[PDB]
Amino acid sequence: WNGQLKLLLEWNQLDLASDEIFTNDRRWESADLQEVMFTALIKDRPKFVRLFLENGLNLQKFLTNEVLTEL
Amino acid sequence: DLVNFIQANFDAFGDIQFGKYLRLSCDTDSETLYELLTQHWHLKTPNLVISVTGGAKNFALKPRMRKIFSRLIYIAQSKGAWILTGGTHYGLMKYIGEVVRDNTISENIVAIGIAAWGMVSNRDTLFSAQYIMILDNNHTHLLLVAKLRNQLEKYISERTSQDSNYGGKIPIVCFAQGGGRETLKAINTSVKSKIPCVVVEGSGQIADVIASLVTSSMVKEKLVRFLPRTVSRLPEEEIESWIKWLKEILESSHLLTVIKMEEAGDEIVSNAISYALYKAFSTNEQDKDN
Amino acid sequence: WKFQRYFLVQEYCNRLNIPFPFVVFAYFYMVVKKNETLAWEGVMKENYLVKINTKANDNSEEMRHRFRQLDSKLNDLKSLLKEIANNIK
Image (tube, rainbow over all chains, first blue to last red; front, top):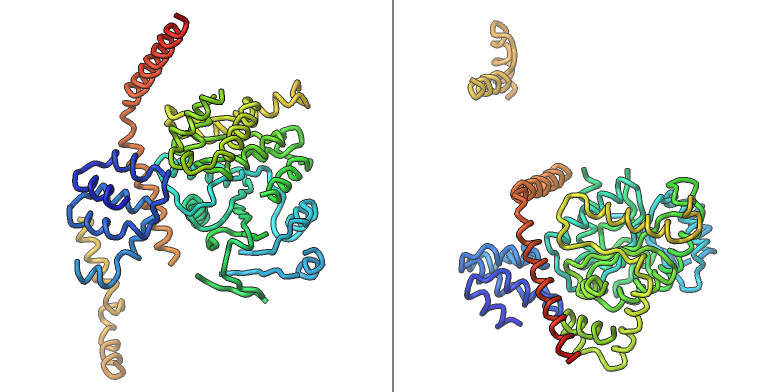
């Protein structure tokens, strides 16, 4: 799941990612998003940020001291 | 006073305020439970809008689903209807709790949530023991113990009501959105009681399957298309059970109302619920010719 | 004018708020001696965002999407009819 999501994120593909990755057929779990979420903040792709926030991500949990320090 | 009665009716009850909570037994009679709840906790409800969602924590919040459920909560508040839900603090349940909080911040909404005692690990037995840490925080009358909820729903439907018209029977509509097996079983058992159920085909995989349905090969193809992983992981025995449950569901076509994807107007949930209740009242053959 | 009115009103409210001829006493005495709202704001923010979304969606361009869906359904029906005809023969 993680590699497929990363590949889809490499290009600006919103609807394809929503349909294929978050179809709900296979549970993805919210904690797994963190890594890719960080990349979305560096690639300057707000729509994937919206996807991650709407798909169960806890933004406050993501903004850990280490994460903010590095960012 | 009330606690003393509860001691004999049920002991081992914990009230938490940060939010009343109770310990439920299968042998517990729904009639006495409803009588006590009306006596001390809440008032008689003109309507009951139950929600069926997969017990799995994983969920997806689409904008259309969010708007639909916000409209549902608004309608429930306007009509003062009870809401029955699993209440495990995940996905749709968490969104419902947040919506209830937002509505109440801006005359009260009942969000009774029935869950399983075993499924939740933390124990905070009692007087008003309060603990933090699965359970939801925004629900008002969560209680811990499928069969119990159906029994309570049928008892409430049988109970006569002096208001809300509907032939002295409370609407008690059943609402089911999303994809799952337990939601299939809940819809089937609700249909067994003739309660009108409304479904949304926008997101729910099994909900979309049923919406598209309205033979065995067709059902298998639809569920494979909409549940590839579930179909592949599901055993051979479970396939026959699912097929029979869905076929029995399709037997009562009139009760099952569906929401169309084309509809995008503000008033969609109210129209669907009203149409379902009208179908149920007209086609029941009892006090329908009036 | 409204901006300057705010400035002057704040200036008057900020000082001792005493009549001019009787302010010396205040000077001498003072020298000698001397989240519900945020939740409501968030709810209104959500309502405002929903209103903006409704204003944007008021375009009413869904007719083309409905027509495309109807055309796809017609094509599927035609394919089913062709399959039935092939099965017959």
